[PDB]
Image (tube, one colour):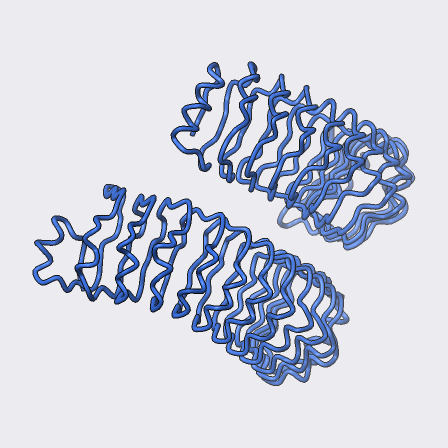
Length: 301
Length: 298
Protein backbone atom coordinates (compact mmCIF):
# COMPACT_ATOMS: atom_id res chain seq x y z
CA UNK A 1 0.00 0.00 0.00
CA UNK A 2 0.88 3.71 0.02
CA UNK A 3 -0.42 7.09 1.15
CA UNK A 4 -0.62 10.73 0.07
CA UNK A 5 2.64 11.84 -1.53
CA UNK A 6 4.09 15.17 -0.45
CA UNK A 7 7.57 15.77 -1.90
CA UNK A 8 6.72 12.45 -3.65
CA UNK A 9 6.61 10.70 -0.22
CA UNK A 10 10.35 10.99 0.59
CA UNK A 11 11.54 10.25 -3.00
CA UNK A 12 9.25 7.12 -2.94
CA UNK A 13 12.21 5.14 -1.38
CA UNK A 14 12.22 2.74 -4.29
CA UNK A 15 9.78 3.76 -7.02
CA UNK A 16 7.39 0.86 -6.34
CA UNK A 17 4.32 2.40 -4.74
CA UNK A 18 1.08 0.54 -5.36
CA UNK A 19 -1.53 2.93 -3.90
CA UNK A 20 -2.03 6.68 -4.15
CA UNK A 21 -3.54 9.85 -2.69
CA UNK A 22 -7.00 11.26 -2.05
CA UNK A 23 -8.44 14.72 -1.90
CA UNK A 24 -9.82 16.44 1.18
CA UNK A 25 -11.26 19.90 1.76
CA UNK A 26 -7.85 21.56 2.22
CA UNK A 27 -6.02 19.66 -0.58
CA UNK A 28 -6.59 21.64 -3.79
CA UNK A 29 -4.49 19.61 -6.32
CA UNK A 30 -5.44 21.49 -9.52
CA UNK A 31 -2.97 19.54 -11.65
CA UNK A 32 -1.23 16.19 -11.43
CA UNK A 33 2.53 16.12 -11.57
CA UNK A 34 3.71 14.37 -14.73
CA UNK A 35 6.13 12.08 -12.82
CA UNK A 36 3.52 9.33 -12.74
CA UNK A 37 5.11 6.77 -15.13
CA UNK A 38 7.95 6.22 -12.58
CA UNK A 39 5.89 4.12 -10.14
CA UNK A 40 5.81 1.15 -12.59
CA UNK A 41 3.51 -1.08 -10.50
CA UNK A 42 0.59 1.11 -9.35
CA UNK A 43 -2.49 -1.08 -9.01
CA UNK A 44 -4.82 1.46 -7.38
CA UNK A 45 -4.87 5.22 -7.89
CA UNK A 46 -7.49 7.35 -6.10
CA UNK A 47 -8.16 11.03 -6.82
CA UNK A 48 -11.46 11.41 -4.99
CA UNK A 49 -12.68 14.98 -4.54
CA UNK A 50 -9.66 16.73 -6.13
CA UNK A 51 -10.24 19.78 -8.33
CA UNK A 52 -8.75 18.13 -11.40
CA UNK A 53 -9.87 19.82 -14.64
CA UNK A 54 -7.56 17.97 -17.08
CA UNK A 55 -5.37 14.90 -17.13
CA UNK A 56 -1.85 14.56 -18.57
CA UNK A 57 -0.94 12.19 -21.36
CA UNK A 58 1.35 10.10 -19.10
CA UNK A 59 -1.65 8.54 -17.31
CA UNK A 60 -2.15 6.30 -20.35
CA UNK A 61 1.27 4.64 -20.45
CA UNK A 62 0.79 3.23 -16.94
CA UNK A 63 -0.45 -0.14 -18.22
CA UNK A 64 0.20 -1.72 -14.89
CA UNK A 65 -2.74 0.30 -13.49
CA UNK A 66 -5.67 -1.83 -12.45
CA UNK A 67 -8.05 0.52 -10.58
CA UNK A 68 -8.39 4.20 -11.38
CA UNK A 69 -10.77 6.44 -9.44
CA UNK A 70 -11.39 9.91 -10.81
CA UNK A 71 -14.52 10.53 -8.68
CA UNK A 72 -15.85 13.94 -7.67
CA UNK A 73 -13.44 15.82 -9.89
CA UNK A 74 -14.69 18.87 -11.83
CA UNK A 75 -13.63 17.49 -15.24
CA UNK A 76 -16.22 18.72 -17.70
CA UNK A 77 -15.19 16.26 -20.45
CA UNK A 78 -14.20 12.58 -20.20
CA UNK A 79 -10.41 12.24 -20.43
CA UNK A 80 -9.57 10.14 -23.48
CA UNK A 81 -6.01 9.92 -22.10
CA UNK A 82 -7.14 6.99 -19.94
CA UNK A 83 -9.03 5.10 -22.67
CA UNK A 84 -5.67 3.66 -23.86
CA UNK A 85 -5.42 1.43 -20.77
CA UNK A 86 -6.45 -1.79 -22.49
CA UNK A 87 -6.19 -3.65 -19.12
CA UNK A 88 -7.98 -1.57 -16.44
CA UNK A 89 -10.12 -3.62 -14.02
CA UNK A 90 -12.06 -0.69 -12.50
CA UNK A 91 -12.90 2.79 -13.76
CA UNK A 92 -14.89 5.11 -11.46
CA UNK A 93 -15.53 8.39 -13.29
CA UNK A 94 -18.53 9.30 -11.06
CA UNK A 95 -19.23 12.78 -9.74
CA UNK A 96 -17.62 14.36 -12.79
CA UNK A 97 -19.74 16.55 -15.05
CA UNK A 98 -20.01 14.60 -18.34
CA UNK A 99 -22.41 15.52 -21.12
CA UNK A 100 -21.21 12.72 -23.42
CA UNK A 101 -19.57 9.31 -22.86
CA UNK A 102 -16.62 9.05 -25.32
CA UNK A 103 -17.08 6.86 -28.35
CA UNK A 104 -13.73 5.07 -27.87
CA UNK A 105 -14.73 3.67 -24.46
CA UNK A 106 -14.90 0.24 -26.15
CA UNK A 107 -11.12 0.31 -26.64
CA UNK A 108 -10.68 -0.56 -22.95
CA UNK A 109 -12.50 -3.97 -23.15
CA UNK A 110 -10.80 -5.26 -19.97
CA UNK A 111 -13.05 -3.36 -17.58
CA UNK A 112 -14.66 -5.31 -14.76
CA UNK A 113 -16.42 -2.56 -12.80
CA UNK A 114 -17.48 0.58 -14.68
CA UNK A 115 -19.02 3.41 -12.64
CA UNK A 116 -20.60 6.07 -14.86
CA UNK A 117 -23.07 7.09 -12.13
CA UNK A 118 -23.88 10.70 -11.06
CA UNK A 119 -23.01 12.02 -14.54
CA UNK A 120 -25.31 14.24 -16.66
CA UNK A 121 -24.91 12.42 -19.98
CA UNK A 122 -27.90 11.88 -22.25
CA UNK A 123 -26.82 8.73 -24.13
CA UNK A 124 -24.47 5.71 -24.04
CA UNK A 125 -22.37 4.78 -27.12
CA UNK A 126 -23.04 1.80 -29.37
CA UNK A 127 -19.49 0.66 -28.44
CA UNK A 128 -20.64 0.18 -24.83
CA UNK A 129 -21.22 -3.41 -26.00
CA UNK A 130 -17.52 -3.78 -26.82
CA UNK A 131 -16.88 -3.93 -23.04
CA UNK A 132 -17.63 -7.64 -23.00
CA UNK A 133 -15.60 -8.33 -19.86
CA UNK A 134 -17.57 -5.94 -17.60
CA UNK A 135 -19.31 -7.34 -14.52
CA UNK A 136 -20.79 -4.27 -12.82
CA UNK A 137 -21.97 -1.22 -14.77
CA UNK A 138 -23.29 1.73 -12.74
CA UNK A 139 -25.46 4.37 -14.43
CA UNK A 140 -27.19 5.67 -11.28
CA UNK A 141 -28.77 9.14 -11.27
CA UNK A 142 -27.70 9.93 -14.84
CA UNK A 143 -29.71 11.66 -17.55
CA UNK A 144 -30.31 8.47 -19.60
CA UNK A 145 -33.25 8.70 -22.00
CA UNK A 146 -32.89 5.03 -23.04
CA UNK A 147 -30.45 2.10 -22.88
CA UNK A 148 -28.80 1.37 -26.26
CA UNK A 149 -29.57 -1.62 -28.46
CA UNK A 150 -26.02 -2.89 -27.77
CA UNK A 151 -26.43 -3.13 -23.97
CA UNK A 152 -27.26 -6.82 -24.52
CA UNK A 153 -23.79 -7.31 -26.04
CA UNK A 154 -22.14 -7.09 -22.59
CA UNK A 155 -22.40 -10.94 -22.35
CA UNK A 156 -20.74 -10.96 -18.90
CA UNK A 157 -22.70 -8.17 -17.13
CA UNK A 158 -23.65 -9.28 -13.62
CA UNK A 159 -24.96 -6.04 -12.11
CA UNK A 160 -26.68 -3.21 -13.97
CA UNK A 161 -27.79 -0.17 -11.98
CA UNK A 162 -29.91 2.61 -13.47
CA UNK A 163 -31.55 4.34 -10.48
CA UNK A 164 -32.72 7.91 -10.96
CA UNK A 165 -32.48 7.71 -14.76
CA UNK A 166 -35.17 9.00 -17.12
CA UNK A 167 -35.69 5.51 -18.52
CA UNK A 168 -39.05 5.50 -20.28
CA UNK A 169 -38.46 2.15 -22.01
CA UNK A 170 -36.20 -0.92 -21.85
CA UNK A 171 -34.65 -2.19 -25.10
CA UNK A 172 -35.86 -5.55 -26.39
CA UNK A 173 -32.22 -6.72 -26.46
CA UNK A 174 -31.91 -6.50 -22.65
CA UNK A 175 -33.00 -10.13 -22.43
CA UNK A 176 -29.75 -11.29 -24.02
CA UNK A 177 -27.81 -10.58 -20.78
CA UNK A 178 -27.53 -14.23 -19.76
CA UNK A 179 -25.17 -13.63 -16.79
CA UNK A 180 -27.09 -10.71 -15.23
CA UNK A 181 -27.64 -11.16 -11.47
CA UNK A 182 -28.62 -7.71 -10.14
CA UNK A 183 -30.80 -5.41 -12.22
CA UNK A 184 -31.73 -2.07 -10.66
CA UNK A 185 -34.37 0.14 -12.34
CA UNK A 186 -35.59 1.81 -9.14
CA UNK A 187 -36.81 5.45 -9.32
CA UNK A 188 -37.11 5.26 -13.13
CA UNK A 189 -40.06 6.04 -15.41
CA UNK A 190 -40.71 2.62 -16.94
CA UNK A 191 -44.35 2.38 -18.02
CA UNK A 192 -43.93 -1.36 -18.65
CA UNK A 193 -41.35 -4.10 -19.15
CA UNK A 194 -40.75 -5.59 -22.60
CA UNK A 195 -41.80 -9.19 -23.20
CA UNK A 196 -38.12 -10.00 -23.84
CA UNK A 197 -37.45 -9.53 -20.09
CA UNK A 198 -37.80 -13.32 -19.66
CA UNK A 199 -34.40 -14.01 -21.23
CA UNK A 200 -32.67 -12.92 -18.00
CA UNK A 201 -32.06 -16.52 -16.94
CA UNK A 202 -29.63 -15.74 -14.10
CA UNK A 203 -31.41 -12.76 -12.43
CA UNK A 204 -31.74 -13.19 -8.65
CA UNK A 205 -32.73 -9.67 -7.54
CA UNK A 206 -34.89 -7.36 -9.66
CA UNK A 207 -35.44 -3.81 -8.40
CA UNK A 208 -38.27 -1.77 -9.92
CA UNK A 209 -39.57 0.23 -6.96
CA UNK A 210 -40.86 3.84 -6.97
CA UNK A 211 -41.27 3.80 -10.75
CA UNK A 212 -44.23 4.43 -13.04
CA UNK A 213 -45.01 0.75 -13.79
CA UNK A 214 -48.65 0.22 -14.79
CA UNK A 215 -48.53 -3.48 -15.77
CA UNK A 216 -46.27 -6.53 -15.78
CA UNK A 217 -45.76 -8.53 -19.00
CA UNK A 218 -46.97 -12.08 -19.58
CA UNK A 219 -43.35 -13.25 -19.97
CA UNK A 220 -41.99 -12.12 -16.57
CA UNK A 221 -42.67 -15.62 -15.12
CA UNK A 222 -40.06 -17.22 -17.37
CA UNK A 223 -37.54 -15.96 -14.75
CA UNK A 224 -37.26 -19.16 -12.74
CA UNK A 225 -34.11 -17.89 -10.93
CA UNK A 226 -35.75 -14.72 -9.54
CA UNK A 227 -35.89 -14.63 -5.73
CA UNK A 228 -36.62 -11.02 -4.64
CA UNK A 229 -38.92 -8.66 -6.54
CA UNK A 230 -39.41 -5.04 -5.42
CA UNK A 231 -42.22 -3.23 -7.25
CA UNK A 232 -43.43 -0.86 -4.54
CA UNK A 233 -44.81 2.66 -4.91
CA UNK A 234 -45.68 2.03 -8.56
CA UNK A 235 -49.01 2.27 -10.38
CA UNK A 236 -49.62 -1.45 -11.03
CA UNK A 237 -53.33 -2.35 -11.25
CA UNK A 238 -53.17 -6.13 -11.77
CA UNK A 239 -50.73 -9.02 -11.85
CA UNK A 240 -50.56 -11.61 -14.66
CA UNK A 241 -51.78 -15.16 -13.97
CA UNK A 242 -48.32 -16.55 -14.79
CA UNK A 243 -46.73 -14.78 -11.75
CA UNK A 244 -47.01 -18.18 -10.01
CA UNK A 245 -44.26 -19.52 -12.31
CA UNK A 246 -41.58 -17.85 -10.12
CA UNK A 247 -40.42 -21.10 -8.51
CA UNK A 248 -37.62 -19.64 -6.35
CA UNK A 249 -39.31 -16.30 -5.46
CA UNK A 250 -39.17 -15.72 -1.71
CA UNK A 251 -39.80 -11.96 -1.37
CA UNK A 252 -42.44 -9.95 -3.23
CA UNK A 253 -43.02 -6.32 -2.32
CA UNK A 254 -46.16 -4.72 -3.74
CA UNK A 255 -46.78 -1.65 -1.58
CA UNK A 256 -48.48 1.44 -2.92
CA UNK A 257 -49.80 -0.04 -6.16
CA UNK A 258 -53.39 0.14 -7.46
CA UNK A 259 -54.00 -3.62 -7.16
CA UNK A 260 -57.63 -4.69 -6.73
CA UNK A 261 -57.28 -8.50 -6.95
CA UNK A 262 -54.62 -11.15 -7.16
CA UNK A 263 -54.59 -14.25 -9.40
CA UNK A 264 -55.37 -17.61 -7.81
CA UNK A 265 -52.04 -18.94 -9.14
CA UNK A 266 -50.11 -17.06 -6.44
CA UNK A 267 -50.76 -20.04 -4.14
CA UNK A 268 -48.38 -22.04 -6.36
CA UNK A 269 -45.54 -20.02 -4.75
CA UNK A 270 -44.27 -22.63 -2.30
CA UNK A 271 -41.04 -20.73 -1.48
CA UNK A 272 -42.62 -17.24 -1.18
CA UNK A 273 -41.74 -16.34 2.41
CA UNK A 274 -42.77 -12.66 2.49
CA UNK A 275 -45.55 -10.81 0.63
CA UNK A 276 -46.11 -7.07 1.14
CA UNK A 277 -49.50 -5.79 -0.03
CA UNK A 278 -50.10 -2.70 2.13
CA UNK A 279 -51.47 0.56 0.66
CA UNK A 280 -53.34 -1.33 -2.10
CA UNK A 281 -57.06 -1.40 -2.85
CA UNK A 282 -58.01 -4.80 -1.42
CA UNK A 283 -61.56 -5.41 -0.25
CA UNK A 284 -61.78 -7.28 3.10
CA UNK A 285 -63.36 -10.35 1.44
CA UNK A 286 -60.46 -10.74 -1.00
CA UNK A 287 -57.90 -10.15 1.78
CA UNK A 288 -59.15 -13.36 3.38
CA UNK A 289 -58.65 -15.12 0.02
CA UNK A 290 -55.03 -13.88 -0.25
CA UNK A 291 -54.39 -15.16 3.29
CA UNK A 292 -56.22 -18.39 2.33
CA UNK A 293 -54.12 -18.99 -0.80
CA UNK A 294 -50.66 -18.51 0.78
CA UNK A 295 -50.74 -19.86 4.36
CA UNK A 296 -46.98 -20.56 4.92
CA UNK A 297 -46.16 -16.94 3.99
CA UNK A 298 -45.57 -14.01 6.34
CA UNK A 299 -47.96 -11.54 4.72
CA UNK A 300 -48.44 -7.86 5.58
CA UNK A 301 -51.38 -5.69 4.53
CA UNK B 1 -68.32 29.72 14.02
CA UNK B 2 -68.60 26.18 15.41
CA UNK B 3 -66.70 23.17 16.76
CA UNK B 4 -66.79 19.37 16.72
CA UNK B 5 -70.16 18.19 18.02
CA UNK B 6 -70.76 15.50 20.65
CA UNK B 7 -74.48 14.79 21.28
CA UNK B 8 -74.56 16.99 18.12
CA UNK B 9 -73.58 20.03 20.24
CA UNK B 10 -76.74 20.21 22.40
CA UNK B 11 -79.30 20.04 19.49
CA UNK B 12 -77.46 23.05 17.91
CA UNK B 13 -78.67 27.68 12.50
CA UNK B 14 -75.10 26.58 13.23
CA UNK B 15 -72.48 27.74 10.71
CA UNK B 16 -69.33 25.48 10.67
CA UNK B 17 -68.57 21.78 11.32
CA UNK B 18 -66.20 19.13 12.79
CA UNK B 19 -62.64 17.77 12.40
CA UNK B 20 -60.77 14.45 12.67
CA UNK B 21 -58.09 13.53 15.28
CA UNK B 22 -56.23 10.41 16.45
CA UNK B 23 -58.99 8.94 18.65
CA UNK B 24 -62.03 10.15 16.66
CA UNK B 25 -62.79 7.37 14.18
CA UNK B 26 -66.10 8.76 12.75
CA UNK B 27 -66.77 6.02 10.19
CA UNK B 28 -69.99 7.51 8.79
CA UNK B 29 -71.92 10.77 8.77
CA UNK B 30 -75.38 10.66 10.29
CA UNK B 31 -78.16 11.55 7.89
CA UNK B 32 -79.31 14.46 10.12
CA UNK B 33 -77.35 17.05 8.17
CA UNK B 34 -80.15 18.71 6.14
CA UNK B 35 -81.42 20.36 9.36
CA UNK B 36 -78.57 22.87 9.69
CA UNK B 37 -79.42 24.87 6.49
CA UNK B 38 -76.87 27.61 7.43
CA UNK B 39 -73.61 25.74 6.77
CA UNK B 40 -71.00 27.85 4.98
CA UNK B 41 -67.98 25.65 5.80
CA UNK B 42 -67.80 21.93 6.56
CA UNK B 43 -64.49 20.23 7.43
CA UNK B 44 -63.96 16.46 7.63
CA UNK B 45 -60.15 16.31 7.43
CA UNK B 46 -58.60 13.07 8.64
CA UNK B 47 -61.87 11.23 9.35
CA UNK B 48 -61.89 7.59 8.24
CA UNK B 49 -64.88 8.20 5.96
CA UNK B 50 -65.65 5.45 3.44
CA UNK B 51 -69.13 6.49 2.19
CA UNK B 52 -71.45 9.49 2.02
CA UNK B 53 -75.26 9.46 2.17
CA UNK B 54 -77.26 11.37 -0.42
CA UNK B 55 -78.54 13.81 2.23
CA UNK B 56 -75.24 15.74 1.88
CA UNK B 57 -76.36 16.94 -1.54
CA UNK B 58 -79.58 18.60 -0.36
CA UNK B 59 -77.74 21.64 1.09
CA UNK B 60 -77.62 24.10 -1.82
CA UNK B 61 -76.51 26.89 0.57
CA UNK B 62 -73.20 25.23 1.53
CA UNK B 63 -70.14 26.91 0.02
CA UNK B 64 -67.02 25.14 1.41
CA UNK B 65 -66.59 21.39 1.97
CA UNK B 66 -63.31 19.68 2.98
CA UNK B 67 -62.84 15.91 2.72
CA UNK B 68 -59.06 15.77 3.25
CA UNK B 69 -57.37 12.49 4.30
CA UNK B 70 -60.46 10.28 4.01
CA UNK B 71 -60.05 6.74 2.64
CA UNK B 72 -62.94 7.05 0.18
CA UNK B 73 -61.85 5.02 -2.84
CA UNK B 74 -64.22 6.70 -5.29
CA UNK B 75 -65.33 10.31 -5.69
CA UNK B 76 -68.76 10.84 -4.05
CA UNK B 77 -71.38 11.55 -6.70
CA UNK B 78 -73.54 13.02 -3.90
CA UNK B 79 -71.52 16.23 -3.81
CA UNK B 80 -71.51 16.94 -7.56
CA UNK B 81 -75.11 18.20 -7.32
CA UNK B 82 -73.96 21.18 -5.20
CA UNK B 83 -74.05 23.66 -8.08
CA UNK B 84 -73.03 26.57 -5.84
CA UNK B 85 -69.97 25.19 -4.05
CA UNK B 86 -67.26 27.81 -3.79
CA UNK B 87 -64.47 25.47 -2.62
CA UNK B 88 -63.91 21.70 -2.82
CA UNK B 89 -60.90 20.00 -1.20
CA UNK B 90 -60.99 16.31 -2.10
CA UNK B 91 -57.24 15.87 -1.34
CA UNK B 92 -55.80 12.86 0.44
CA UNK B 93 -58.60 10.55 -0.76
CA UNK B 94 -57.49 7.65 -2.96
CA UNK B 95 -59.08 8.48 -6.31
CA UNK B 96 -58.30 6.62 -9.51
CA UNK B 97 -60.70 8.62 -11.69
CA UNK B 98 -62.17 12.10 -11.51
CA UNK B 99 -65.85 11.75 -12.56
CA UNK B 100 -66.98 13.12 -15.88
CA UNK B 101 -69.90 14.85 -14.08
CA UNK B 102 -67.56 17.22 -12.19
CA UNK B 103 -68.62 19.91 -14.70
CA UNK B 104 -72.16 19.85 -13.25
CA UNK B 105 -70.79 21.78 -10.26
CA UNK B 106 -69.54 24.73 -12.43
CA UNK B 107 -69.67 27.24 -9.58
CA UNK B 108 -66.35 26.18 -8.09
CA UNK B 109 -63.74 28.81 -7.28
CA UNK B 110 -60.97 26.74 -5.66
CA UNK B 111 -60.59 23.04 -6.49
CA UNK B 112 -58.01 20.97 -4.61
CA UNK B 113 -57.62 17.62 -6.38
CA UNK B 114 -54.04 17.19 -5.15
CA UNK B 115 -52.44 14.08 -3.56
CA UNK B 116 -54.75 11.74 -5.49
CA UNK B 117 -53.74 8.80 -7.71
CA UNK B 118 -55.88 9.71 -10.72
CA UNK B 119 -54.51 9.03 -14.18
CA UNK B 120 -56.50 11.48 -16.31
CA UNK B 121 -58.74 14.48 -15.85
CA UNK B 122 -62.14 14.37 -17.60
CA UNK B 123 -62.79 16.61 -20.59
CA UNK B 124 -65.55 18.40 -18.61
CA UNK B 125 -62.80 20.02 -16.49
CA UNK B 126 -63.11 22.98 -18.90
CA UNK B 127 -66.82 23.40 -18.07
CA UNK B 128 -65.76 24.85 -14.67
CA UNK B 129 -65.41 28.36 -16.07
CA UNK B 130 -65.59 30.03 -12.66
CA UNK B 131 -62.59 28.19 -11.14
CA UNK B 132 -59.71 30.32 -9.84
CA UNK B 133 -57.17 27.95 -8.26
CA UNK B 134 -56.84 24.32 -9.32
CA UNK B 135 -54.38 22.20 -7.36
CA UNK B 136 -53.22 18.98 -9.01
CA UNK B 137 -50.07 18.44 -6.94
CA UNK B 138 -48.50 14.97 -6.69
CA UNK B 139 -51.10 13.27 -8.88
CA UNK B 140 -50.58 10.64 -11.58
CA UNK B 141 -51.32 13.00 -14.48
CA UNK B 142 -49.68 11.93 -17.73
CA UNK B 143 -51.01 15.05 -19.52
CA UNK B 144 -53.44 17.91 -19.05
CA UNK B 145 -56.60 17.54 -21.16
CA UNK B 146 -57.20 19.61 -24.28
CA UNK B 147 -60.00 21.40 -22.41
CA UNK B 148 -57.71 22.74 -19.63
CA UNK B 149 -57.54 26.02 -21.58
CA UNK B 150 -61.33 26.35 -21.49
CA UNK B 151 -61.34 27.37 -17.80
CA UNK B 152 -61.01 31.11 -18.73
CA UNK B 153 -60.74 32.17 -15.09
CA UNK B 154 -57.94 29.92 -13.82
CA UNK B 155 -55.65 32.26 -11.92
CA UNK B 156 -53.40 29.73 -10.16
CA UNK B 157 -52.53 26.26 -11.48
CA UNK B 158 -50.34 23.79 -9.55
CA UNK B 159 -49.17 20.48 -10.96
CA UNK B 160 -46.12 19.69 -8.81
CA UNK B 161 -44.98 16.09 -8.76
CA UNK B 162 -47.16 15.17 -11.74
CA UNK B 163 -45.76 13.02 -14.54
CA UNK B 164 -46.43 15.68 -17.17
CA UNK B 165 -44.50 14.71 -20.29
CA UNK B 166 -45.95 17.58 -22.34
CA UNK B 167 -48.13 20.67 -21.96
CA UNK B 168 -51.17 21.00 -24.26
CA UNK B 169 -51.14 23.50 -27.11
CA UNK B 170 -54.38 24.94 -25.70
CA UNK B 171 -52.66 25.99 -22.44
CA UNK B 172 -52.07 29.40 -24.02
CA UNK B 173 -55.78 30.26 -23.96
CA UNK B 174 -55.69 30.71 -20.16
CA UNK B 175 -55.72 34.50 -20.35
CA UNK B 176 -56.19 34.99 -16.58
CA UNK B 177 -53.44 32.58 -15.44
CA UNK B 178 -51.21 34.32 -12.87
CA UNK B 179 -49.44 31.47 -11.02
CA UNK B 180 -48.22 28.38 -12.87
CA UNK B 181 -46.38 25.74 -10.85
CA UNK B 182 -44.96 22.91 -12.94
CA UNK B 183 -42.14 22.11 -10.51
CA UNK B 184 -40.97 18.45 -10.14
CA UNK B 185 -42.66 17.54 -13.44
CA UNK B 186 -41.14 15.82 -16.49
CA UNK B 187 -41.57 18.42 -19.23
CA UNK B 188 -38.85 18.01 -21.85
CA UNK B 189 -39.85 21.41 -23.31
CA UNK B 190 -42.60 24.01 -23.32
CA UNK B 191 -44.91 24.36 -26.32
CA UNK B 192 -44.59 27.51 -28.42
CA UNK B 193 -48.21 28.40 -27.45
CA UNK B 194 -46.92 29.24 -23.94
CA UNK B 195 -46.64 32.85 -25.18
CA UNK B 196 -50.41 33.16 -24.84
CA UNK B 197 -50.07 33.31 -21.03
CA UNK B 198 -50.52 37.07 -20.93
CA UNK B 199 -51.21 37.42 -17.21
CA UNK B 200 -48.54 35.07 -15.77
CA UNK B 201 -46.39 36.75 -13.11
CA UNK B 202 -44.81 33.66 -11.46
CA UNK B 203 -43.66 30.60 -13.45
CA UNK B 204 -42.26 27.62 -11.56
CA UNK B 205 -40.54 24.94 -13.64
CA UNK B 206 -37.74 23.93 -11.27
CA UNK B 207 -36.51 20.34 -10.67
CA UNK B 208 -37.92 19.18 -14.00
CA UNK B 209 -36.46 17.74 -17.20
CA UNK B 210 -36.55 20.88 -19.38
CA UNK B 211 -34.01 20.57 -22.19
CA UNK B 212 -34.89 23.82 -23.92
CA UNK B 213 -36.95 26.94 -23.65
CA UNK B 214 -39.19 27.88 -26.59
CA UNK B 215 -38.57 30.99 -28.64
CA UNK B 216 -41.93 32.48 -27.63
CA UNK B 217 -41.17 32.67 -23.89
CA UNK B 218 -40.18 36.29 -24.44
CA UNK B 219 -43.80 37.14 -25.27
CA UNK B 220 -44.58 36.95 -21.51
CA UNK B 221 -44.18 40.66 -20.79
CA UNK B 222 -45.95 40.34 -17.41
CA UNK B 223 -43.67 37.52 -16.19
CA UNK B 224 -41.63 38.63 -13.19
CA UNK B 225 -40.17 35.48 -11.59
CA UNK B 226 -38.88 32.46 -13.53
CA UNK B 227 -37.64 29.42 -11.61
CA UNK B 228 -35.87 26.93 -13.87
CA UNK B 229 -33.24 25.57 -11.53
CA UNK B 230 -32.09 21.92 -11.49
CA UNK B 231 -33.23 21.34 -15.07
CA UNK B 232 -31.35 20.09 -18.15
CA UNK B 233 -31.29 23.39 -20.06
CA UNK B 234 -28.32 23.71 -22.44
CA UNK B 235 -28.96 27.18 -23.91
CA UNK B 236 -31.30 30.15 -23.55
CA UNK B 237 -33.30 31.70 -26.41
CA UNK B 238 -32.37 35.13 -27.74
CA UNK B 239 -35.94 36.26 -26.91
CA UNK B 240 -35.13 36.03 -23.17
CA UNK B 241 -34.31 39.76 -23.47
CA UNK B 242 -37.97 40.54 -24.14
CA UNK B 243 -38.99 39.78 -20.52
CA UNK B 244 -39.05 43.44 -19.47
CA UNK B 245 -40.76 42.87 -16.10
CA UNK B 246 -38.62 39.85 -15.14
CA UNK B 247 -36.79 40.63 -11.91
CA UNK B 248 -35.79 37.13 -10.72
CA UNK B 249 -34.27 34.43 -12.93
CA UNK B 250 -33.10 31.21 -11.24
CA UNK B 251 -30.93 28.88 -13.32
CA UNK B 252 -29.04 26.59 -10.91
CA UNK B 253 -27.92 23.12 -11.91
CA UNK B 254 -28.49 23.27 -15.66
CA UNK B 255 -26.02 22.47 -18.45
CA UNK B 256 -25.72 26.08 -19.73
CA UNK B 257 -22.51 26.99 -21.55
CA UNK B 258 -23.32 30.56 -22.68
CA UNK B 259 -25.96 33.26 -22.36
CA UNK B 260 -27.45 35.45 -25.11
CA UNK B 261 -26.15 39.01 -25.34
CA UNK B 262 -29.79 40.22 -25.03
CA UNK B 263 -29.86 39.43 -21.28
CA UNK B 264 -28.45 42.94 -20.68
CA UNK B 265 -31.75 44.38 -21.97
CA UNK B 266 -33.35 43.29 -18.67
CA UNK B 267 -33.14 46.54 -16.72
CA UNK B 268 -35.57 45.23 -14.08
CA UNK B 269 -33.65 41.96 -13.52
CA UNK B 270 -32.36 42.46 -9.97
CA UNK B 271 -31.33 38.92 -8.98
CA UNK B 272 -29.80 36.12 -11.11
CA UNK B 273 -28.75 32.59 -10.11
CA UNK B 274 -26.25 30.84 -12.39
CA UNK B 275 -24.36 28.56 -9.99
CA UNK B 276 -23.63 24.88 -10.81
CA UNK B 277 -23.48 25.72 -14.55
CA UNK B 278 -20.79 25.19 -17.18
CA UNK B 279 -19.54 28.78 -17.39
CA UNK B 280 -15.88 29.42 -18.18
CA UNK B 281 -14.22 32.40 -16.40
CA UNK B 282 -14.14 34.29 -19.72
CA UNK B 283 -17.93 33.97 -20.05
CA UNK B 284 -18.64 34.72 -16.36
CA UNK B 285 -16.88 38.08 -16.77
CA UNK B 286 -19.03 38.87 -19.83
CA UNK B 287 -22.27 37.93 -18.01
CA UNK B 288 -21.47 40.17 -15.00
CA UNK B 289 -20.47 42.93 -17.45
CA UNK B 290 -23.76 42.70 -19.42
CA UNK B 291 -26.29 43.20 -16.63
CA UNK B 292 -24.66 45.74 -14.27
CA UNK B 293 -27.51 46.61 -11.82
CA UNK B 294 -28.22 42.93 -11.15
CA UNK B 295 -26.99 41.03 -8.12
CA UNK B 296 -25.54 37.95 -9.77
CA UNK B 297 -24.54 34.63 -8.19
CA UNK B 298 -22.25 32.04 -9.80
